[PDB]
Image (cartoon, rainbow, N blue to C red; front, side, top):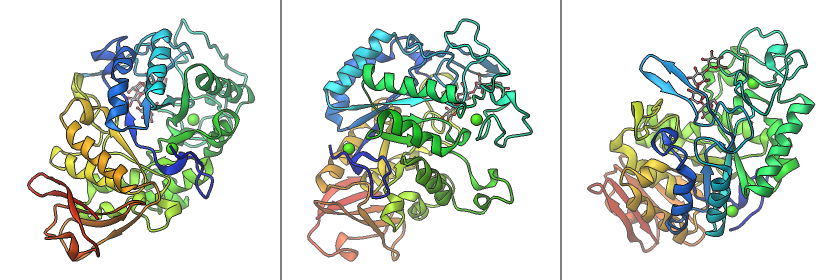
Length: 418
Ligand SMILES: OC[C@H]1O[C@H](O[C@H]2[C@H](O)[C@@H](O)[C@@H](O[C@H]3[C@H](O)[C@@H](O)[C@@H](O[C@H]4[C@H](O)[C@@H](O)[C@@H](O)O[C@@H]4CO)O[C@@H]3CO)O[C@@H]2CO)[C@H](O)[C@@H](O)[C@@H]1O
Ligand SMILES: [Ca+2]
Ligand SMILES: [Ca+2]
């Protein structure tokens, strides 16, 4: 495990990570208080599958609850009330065992942290911040979903649960918890939640103070049309918007540019995600994914959230693309362990590693065929990737002696290594 910072000091940890999102939206409903026991038990498997890191659910207990017609949710971690680790995923004790088992097997533990808001209203909690002290966004005049004097970012829905993460005491509180996660819960890094909610610069601060040399990733889902008309971002590409967050937080960022192309364009247009960017300083900070707990389905109730789900006819192509290309790939728990894509994914992980493909590896796109046709310059081998293409042989697009590495879905997924 190579471990440095990128050339622009972004915390990509060697640019060689392969991450597993370790949960789906309905875990708290399907394996109540049993999730950490399940991970402990699966640690060796996760490690053998080839993952170098795992994105853990929020560790802070969440006993929230909501209902919206047929829709229902709560307890998943995004509306926590305390730093107490005895939540719906399992106890503190189990968490410790789980992180220890993962860590021992050589899988880094990345915690999902939610600094933007908390469950203000929860009656029995250990963290009680009174009103009128500047701790809350709503301590200030709250015009609309725009930064206010009590919160330098967007608000979460109503904004009544928004924290002034910039308040010296609120900042300090998060900072200590981050340090706590690293020293007693074996944190090798963090996934920063709802990043649009507070300044990017705060994320760099936090990382600097508690885990400067760790891995970090920001979850920024905000399209151009959500910025004010006068803002440059209102006219920028998805790529520019996320790259800008990354420059400021000094953390890799989820590639929502690739996700939007996967949902709205053709497979040939997948080349316009951050990860396909010709400048290595651009593509290396991209954290690729096919679906997450928000965008995809989940086993159980209501099929989870499925806000921007990738259709099944493209799941193999999508994994083939992310696992063989630049940026840092993320595998969704369900595709891997629930839905039967596990074998195919395992094969690609092996291909990626044998080729020595990394965050900054070069990628070239070949124009004369149908589908996506790309040449990837791994540090050990060159890969030719042809997805839903009329390409006949790797030699039509690259110099060298190629061997078939992968051939799935009636040749819709073809990968060759030199
Ligand atoms: O007190 C503040 C607000 O509280 C109430 O909001 C409810 C919402 O209406 C519910 O829908 C729900 O919210 C979920 C959200 O549905 C779910 O997607 C998840 O969101 C995360 C997301 O996973 C994550 O990836 C990330 O980037 O950001 C999101 C926020 O962290 O989790 C949310 C919280 O559980 O629950 C909230 C609170 O219970 C109320 O309705 C509002 O009026 C009020 O302002
Ligand atoms: Ca690394
Ligand atoms: Ca906010």
